[PDB]
Image (cartoon, helix red, strand yellow):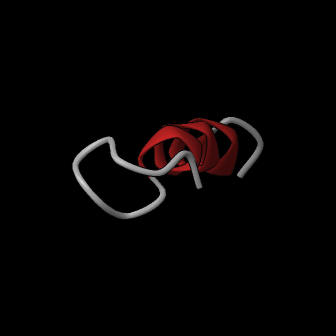
Amino acid sequence: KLGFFKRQYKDMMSEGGPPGAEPQ
């Protein structure tokens, strides 16, 4: 998993759900 969740977590950390609205 090392590397799969790290990249998927950092990608959603900037979008936070919306199209790049809230960094979550």
Dividing the picture into quadrants, the one containing residue 2 is: top right
Rendering quarter of residue 23: top right
Q: Is residue 2 left or right of residue 22?
A: right
Q: Nearer the viewer, residue 22 or 4?
A: 22
Determine whether, in the image, residue 10 is placed left or right of residue 21: right
Identify whether 20 is placed above or below 17: above
x and y percent of residue 14 in the render? 51, 39
Q: Position of residue 16 (x, y in %)?
A: 48, 57
Residue 13, how many percent across, how many down? 59, 46
- Give the residue displayed 35% in from the left and 47% down from the top: 21
Residue 17's spot in the image, x, y percent? Answer: 38, 64
Residue 14 versus residue 12 in the image, above or below: above
Residue at x-position 61% and y-position 49%: 9
Q: Residue furthest right?
A: 2
Question: Residue at position x 41%, y 47% from top?
Answer: 15
Closest to the observer, 14 or 5 = 14
